[PDB]
Structure formats: structure tokens, C-alpha cells
Image (cartoon, coloured by chain):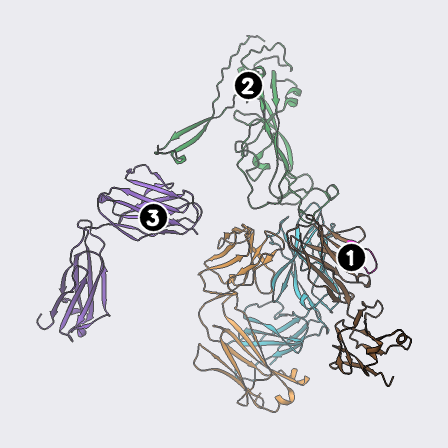
Chain colours: A orange, B brown, C purple, D green, E cyan
Amino acid sequence: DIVMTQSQKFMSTSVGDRVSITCKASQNVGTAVAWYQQKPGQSPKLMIYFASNRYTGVPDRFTGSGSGTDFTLTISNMQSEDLADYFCQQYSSYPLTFGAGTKLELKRADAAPTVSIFPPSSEQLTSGGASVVCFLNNFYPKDINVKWKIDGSERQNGVLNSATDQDSKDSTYSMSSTLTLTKDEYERHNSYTCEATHKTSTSPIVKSFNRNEC
Amino acid sequence: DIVMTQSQKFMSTSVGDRVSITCKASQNVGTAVAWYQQKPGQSPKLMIYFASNRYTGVPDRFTGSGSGTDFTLTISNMQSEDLADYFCQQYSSYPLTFGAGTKLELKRADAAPTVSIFPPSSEQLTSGGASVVCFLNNFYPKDINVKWKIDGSERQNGVLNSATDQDSKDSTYSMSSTLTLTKDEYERHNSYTCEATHKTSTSPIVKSFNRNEC
Amino acid sequence: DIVMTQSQKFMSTSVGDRVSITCKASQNVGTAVAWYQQKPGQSPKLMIYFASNRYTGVPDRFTGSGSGTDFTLTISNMQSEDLADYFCQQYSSYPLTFGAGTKLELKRADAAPTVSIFPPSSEQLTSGGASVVCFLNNFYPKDINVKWKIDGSERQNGVLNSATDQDSKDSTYSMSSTLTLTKDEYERHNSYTCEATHKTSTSPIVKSFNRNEC
Amino acid sequence: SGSGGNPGQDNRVNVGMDYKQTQLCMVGCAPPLGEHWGKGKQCTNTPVQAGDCPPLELITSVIQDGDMVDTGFGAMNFADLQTNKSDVPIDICGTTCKYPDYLQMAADPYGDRLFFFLRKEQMFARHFFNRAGEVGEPVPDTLIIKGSGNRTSVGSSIYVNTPSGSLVSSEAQLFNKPYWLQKAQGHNNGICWGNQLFVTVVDTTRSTNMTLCASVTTSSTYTNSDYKEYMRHVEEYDLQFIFQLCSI
Amino acid sequence: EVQLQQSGAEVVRSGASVKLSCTASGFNIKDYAIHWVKQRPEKGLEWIGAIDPEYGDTEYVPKFQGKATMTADTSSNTAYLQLSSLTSEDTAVYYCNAGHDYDRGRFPYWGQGTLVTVSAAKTTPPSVYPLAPGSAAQTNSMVTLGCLVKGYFPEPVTVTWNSGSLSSGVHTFPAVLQSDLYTLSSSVTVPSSTWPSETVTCNVAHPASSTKVDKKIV
């Protein structure tokens, strides 16, 4: 069993720069190494095969190299469409093995998030449940903290967070935070507040609503 | 002398499950490895030979694999008729060698043993000898320890143990323990005790009798 | 990557003597080693190629030798025209690699330095800046230390040093040291001293001036 | 025999060989006809590409001075039928090998192209090997029992043999001796219509290629970098004719 | 025009077999070397085996021998992959790949992917909830709208808005598993002159259950 060991699981870079991904073999495999690209929610696409041969399709931007046990994929000048996972594969002997995932992220400049709070819909409040959502869209970097306030008091239980990966088009990130309460508990308080603190501002972005006024 | 080392002597599983038996060689033997099945009281039957070739007879249920020094027999979904011993054999160079036995067993369910102690019969005491027997019937798993006490003191010499194999009907085990003493020594003590300790109970099962009272 | 490791960066000798430069390979390269000569301000010229074969030219004065991993260039009797850099190169496998620089120098030793200190010109003091220079001319060997004193106190910040290579005519070395301060800072001290310590004298050569007296 | 399993990117090897021995000469008042197999007009049956076997068509054409004779691989257009430019030696891999269409030139009414002809072809199978690359048409399952634990991959079943012209001798020579056109096979009994005569000649018995070596420098020792190697071939002919005046 | 269609996602209880199919790889005279790859969210990609139509040759991995069975129908068709005793470690996305004509390394032609979920419970349809702004404290410019998908099983769900129209300014958030049920969120940003001027509707398609359509109103 030939083990494919890729250096880093994640990789940082910026638009236009040059990136090199390394793949180390546990045995000599000559040039029987292939590289693949996989975007989220899609099937992998072949990029390089036979160490340094581009497949029909793949731009000269991508170049493979290496032999024996050290192999490298190089991306000379980048585009937003290159944000995906990159795998190396060995086919010198059975069984065929792949390397660990490698995520390529962009270092593009840092935007402040856009925060929108939404009270529970009238339809969901008829089911006995109440979900308050708070969308944080198009921010960079990834580090961000969301704080839920119910009548000014911080609420810890009942929060569900879902962070999006880096957007393939503008290199931004998104996050959804959902506070799910029972209708009885939702109707016992008035003020609901979603506060987002991010390094792009020294004061948190506050979005709030009142149950009585809305 | 190429040594055939099989991992475990016993293996537990249930009908329908998937079992894999491993056989490790002390030398490279390519694919010159054969597997056999032997039921109690019968001669072994050839199953797989040349690492992964089934013999005329053997269902597709059995699959062999491996090369060089690691070989494996896999049973994809089981039947009751597959409970037997399995051996691996090397025929790369003389002398031919076999692996240790490997018993495939059914697990069933966890029973506590049934302990019955029997003093020497009046007929055997006419011959100058005295045998105290202790039957441990229908227990699982196999691991169990019997302790003989004479007037509360543990007795080591003179014990003969006979463990039964797995019952073909209810998958339980049985064990007989016989303490054989001279009549002179038997009549010099009063209390005789047979204690069975098993994982199904945190206290030993105690069966005892007194010579004077019986 | 085959690493070319040359022994010494600099080498001393005199006209007529015999010089041997060594080049050690990190791998066996047979005889696929070439030697080059590079004079300052010019492009390198090949001397020996295939370890020990002279290129069209090239005086029999130069002789190459070695095989496998130890290679040597020998200059049996020298001329002034041989003072230059010498490189060894491997071409057994890609990528091609070269060795570190090796300077061949003449050892006509030894002179004591000539130290001259110059206060900032009246013209430079009109721009708000003040540079004090100290020339150390025609000394040997290269090892020399300059110490700046402002009112007797050693000054570390603001010094710029520029060492000259060996002079092609008399085999001596030169060094310039410039202490650059603001005019405000220059006019706040009186005594400025440049001290040169060199192995040709057990006491430093001291050149000084006073701002008020000059 | 051999060899296990090394199919890869590029398995091409530097290989040399000698061709099949061929001597022939023809005379007529019209140029000769040659036949060769080329990429045929598309297509017999229908309809789709790609990378499939190209349709074959037997093309009859006029043999020009400089066209290649058959070697040991048939009369075909290697430029179109072999797209890898690497299946046959370099002197035929980019051209076309033409073979004389004796049947057509003999069956034409007037017979202006064949006053007579002489020929001698000979060859044997020197070595055998298989082609690298994907098998376009694999062996049917009924003809091979698949294995094998290992193996499992059917080896390349595209076999081709190198030719060899065998012995060349003076007793086998067709030339340097006169030929008298006593009777012609066609109706044209040696009449040179248009006051012209086409004489076709193929002679592989004098195909020796001379090797030239020029020195760029002369190092103290022997170094291959000091010399350039060249290939040169020569052909010497002397055409002698004797004509008879005729009136009509 | 060289794409591979598979069987489709399936929810199976533990201890039952499942059969996956492929298409347009495996013809007479041609020739292909079909491979199958398993994608576990933790182990990355794992090669299963290599099958050759026109011969029916079979090669497996010792890890999957006895777990995966491979078959090939020469007419049409090809390539069936079936798994026997399904456990929790078999919950993965399986791909049918064919390097052009032959060989191992090359997978330039991948299948669409088939998500197999081996677990108990049963397919629960999603509850879609609109996420509209609050009163009149927003106005111009541009408005964010959302649809909340809660309490469904299994992954995935397909969330679209204007019937495929308008793909810019949308954000699909990864699902979160809580109480053995999934929860998805989706947001879209449109100019204030668009909503509520023209209707905005989100569509939630759940292949193992039911498609839903919900329009957003003030």
C-alpha cells in the first residue's frame, strides 16, 4: 500500500500569485502520478496525468513536475475559478491510493460583513416553534464572532451556526446563525439582537428588532 | 522453514456477518498459499489455492487474497455450515508448513453456568477411592475458573478438568471437574466446595456439601 | 538535486605557485563535471569539461582531475591573468547545479592601512545632513575593524561600510566607512574619532578632529 | 518472450533495420501506374468519430521520380494511416510507398505503359515486436481465457515484423545487361508515341549509405563532441537505348 | 457528449444490500477500464476496483473484497456496483469513472456521483420557512431574503430561487446536523426596486422526499 502524503491540508495565496502543492510517495512510482481538481458539490476533474502531461481541457496555467517519490503541482498566476480541492493519485501498483485533501484559499482584501436579521415567520409561529436567523454575508477574513441577545441578555443555548467556504467568485465568506426557541419562550421576550464583531471595525455591527413593534 | 503465523486461535461472529482470517508468512512465498476447511471428526477439505483461486466445489462466498507475506481469507455473509477450523498452507519451498488452528464460532447470548456438585458414590468408596465431580453446563463465553475447597482450603493436586467444545444446538459450553482422593484422605475432612467464577456474575457460584451431613 | 560543495571561498597564492581547487559532489556523477573561469564584469568562460578535457583554447597550465564525487582543478604555475572566480558544474542529471564561488588572490603581504578622516563638507551642511567619512587604503590582510567615537563614546547606528576587493596592481585592500548624522546631531558634539585596528600593529591607528577647531 | 507489464507514457525505442530487396525496370511511352492504400473517402457505413480506424482505399496513381518503393510494411500512405509519425522508419513515415499496378497496366487496351517489365522481390521476417498504445480492436472474449490474479491486462496484440532483404549477389542482377524488345505484351510494340519514353527503375542492391565524419575540433583525448556525423547516399546510372525508325 | 449517469441517491437501513449502476461506459469492441471511487467525508477518496468491459476482468482492493461486488453487462450498459452488509462506514458518495479507452491513473470522465446513506430512521421531508424583513426599518438599498430548511433527512436538498433565474447574490450555507436531523439555510440579495415589486419564490427539492415552493411576502 503506497501512501500518498500531501504537505498541508489548507493553503493560502492571493490572486495572481504562484502556488505549489507537494505530494510525497512512500515508494518509487516513477512518473505514474495523476492530479485532480474537485470543486464543492461537483465530481473531480482530471488535470494532470503521467506526472507532467496536461489533459485535453486544462490550461497551460497548470504545470506538473516530479518523479520517483516527490511530485509537485504548480499554478503560475491564479484565477478565482481555481479555488477547489487538489488530489494526487498513484497508479504504479495496486491498490490505487490518493492523497489527503488540499484546500486552496485566496488572500484577497478584507471586506466588512453585511448583517441581516429575520424574525420567525408567521407560518413557523403557527407550528409552536420560533427560529431567528442572522445572515453574515461577504466578509473577510474568516475570524468572526456572533452574539445573540434576548432583552439585552446573552443567549448561549439554542444557537446553530453554519459557516460557508470561500466563495469561488469574490473570495468572501458567509455565515448563518439560527436561534431556535419554542413559541412560548419567544413570546415571553421583546428585544432580539444579533451582533457581529469583526476585525474590519472596532465596534460590533448590531441588527435588532422588537417583537411588539414587529 | 517458513513459519505460518495465524493471528487469532478463535474468532467470534454471527450468521450473515463478514469474517476475515489473516495468515502471515515468515518469508516471501509469492502466491503459493492454500486454504483448507476442517470440521470436527472429518478430514480437511481444500478451499482456496494459489492465493485467490477457488477449488471446484467451493461457493463464491469464500474469497482468498494476499501476496508475498500477508494473506487473507474472507467469508462475505455466513451460514451455519461454515463453523469449522481454517488452515493456511505454504508451498513455495520444502518443507511444506501449515498455520495454527483458527476456530470460527457463533456468539449467541450470555448465559450463566449451571453448577452441580456430586460427592463420591457409596460404591466407589468400597474400592478405596473417592472422586468428587462438579459439572458446569451451558455457559458462555469459554473463560471460566473452577476452585476446589477442602474445609475452606484451596486444593490444587488431584484435579482433572475436561472442557467441552461449543454445542451444535445452543452454542453453549460445558466443563467437568473431578477431584480424586483416596478414601482415607476423603474421610479426614468434612467440607467440600466447588466454586465457579464467570464473567456473567461478579460473585462466584458456590456449591458445597458436608461429608458428615451427607 | 545534486549539491556542488567547493571547499574554500577564497584562496591565497603567488605568481608561479601551484593551486588546487576541490569540488565535492553529493552524488556519483561519473565524469560529467565542468569548470569555468569568471573575471569581474565579464561573462564566464569554460576551462575544463568532461572532468579532465580542455576546451578549444586553453593553456595546458590548467588541468582537471577526479571522478565520481571528488573533482579537482590544478593550475601548475600561475600568471596574473588567472586571478578570477572558478566554478564547478554537474550535468549528470537535471537540474544542473553549480558550486559556490572561489576567488584566487595574490598574497604579497603585508602593508598597514592608511587612515584619513574627513568632516562633513560645508556644502552638505546646507542640506541638513552631515556625513563623516574614513578611508582605510592599501592594507593587508582583509581582517580589519573600524570603531567610530563621538565625544569618546562608541557610535553604532548610522555607519555604512564598503570594502573593496583585492587591487589588481599591488594586491592590497581598501575600505570606506561613512557615519551619516543629521546636522542638528552633528553640531551637538565636538570630538569625532575614527580608529582602525589591524594585525600589523598592536595599537589602533587613530584619526580625529574637533568640530569647534575645524 | 517478454515482457511483463511496462505500458507507459512513451515506450518508443531507437531501432534500425534493412529493407526488402527489390529490383525492377519498365519501359513505355506513358508513365507507369502505382497502387497504394490510403485514407479512403469517408465513409462506408455511418456516421461517427473519433480516433477510429480510417477507411482504406486502394489508390492508383502515376509513379513519379522520387516516390518510395515498398519496404517491409506494404504500399500505403503512412502520413495519413499512421498519425504518430513513429511506426515506421523516418524515410517512409512522412511519405507514401507505392507498388506497381502490374494488373491494371497489363489490362489496358493500348498498353502504352508496359512495353515490358522485369522484377525481383525478396524478403524474410527478421524480428518481431508489438506496438505501444491502446488496442483499437481488442481480441474477442471467445478467443482468450482471461487471467490471472496478476496479468489480467491483455498484452498489445498489434504485431509487426521487421523485413530483411537477405543476400544481394551479382547473379541476381537485372541491370548491366541489354534487353531486346522482341515482342511486347500489349498492342504497342515499342512505339514511342509523342517522341518520348518513360523508363522506370528500382534498384535496392546498391543502397549502401556512406557515413561521413567531420571534425569540429581535435581535443588532446578522444571526445565525441569534436565530430559531426553525416549520412550520404549516391546513385550512378547510364541509360543506353537503340531505336528503329518507322513510318506510318 | 461523454458523461456518465448513475443510479441515484438511496437511503438504506443497516444490514441490507444496495446496487449502483453506471451508463455509457462499457460497449462491445470498446474497451474501457471502468473504476469505482468511494468518497467518505473523513477519508477522502478511496479506490474500489477496476473492471474491463469486453472482458469482464475484475480487480479489487483487499479492504473491499467481500464488501463490494462488481458486474458488467456487455450489451448497453455497465457498470453495476453492489455492496452487501451495509454499515455506518459505507455512508459515502460513489463515483463511476472511466479513463478514455484503458488504463488506471486516468479518470477524465467521472460519473455524476451517488450518495448512499446507511442508517436507521426514515426519510423525513423538509420544513421550509420564509425569512422576510421586519416592518419598515430597512428600505433602500438592496434587500436580503432567505428560506430556512429545517428538520429533514437525508442530505442533500436543492434550493433554487426564481426558477433557476438570478444566480448572483445567492448564498447556500452548509447543513448542520442536530437531533439526527439536518438544517439548511439559503439567502439571496436583490435590489429594493425588485422586491416586493416582483415576486420572489424559493424552491426546495428533496430527492428522497418532496419538492416545495414558497413565495416571500411582506
- Subunit of label 1: B
Mark 1 Cα-neighbour bin, 10 Å: few <14, some 14–19, many ≥20: some
Q: Are marks 3 and 1 in contact (CB under 8 Å)?
A: no
- Subunit of label 3: C
Q: Mark 1 points at which residue?
A: B37
Residue at the bottom extreme of this rendering:
A188
- The answer to whether residue C122 is seen in the rendering is no
The residue drawn where x is 73% and y is 65% is B11
Q: Distance between the residues labelled 3 and 1?
A: 69 Å
> What's the mark number on residue C22?
3
> What is the three-letter code of the residue carrying label 3?
Thr
Whether C49 is drawn above or below A46: the answer is above
- The picture places residue A15, in percent across and down from the top left corner, at 45, 63
Q: Distance between the residues labelled 2 and 1?
A: 85 Å
Residue span colored magenta:
B37-46
Name the residue nearer the viewer: D164 or B68: B68
Q: What secondary structure is the magenta-colored segment mainly?
A: loop
- Subunit of label 2: D
Name the residue nearer the viewer: B153 or B203: B153
Image side of residue B177 versus residue A166, left or right: right
Q: Name the residue under label 2.
A: D198
Indicate yes or no whether the magenta region holds residue C169.
no
Circle 1 sits in a helix, a strand or a loop, which is it?
strand
> What's the mark number on residue C201?
none
Indicate yes or no whether the magenta region holds residue B42.
yes
The residue drawn where x is 17% and y is 50% is C170
> What is the three-letter code of the residue carrying label 1?
Gln
Q: Distance between the residues labelled 2 and 3?
A: 72 Å
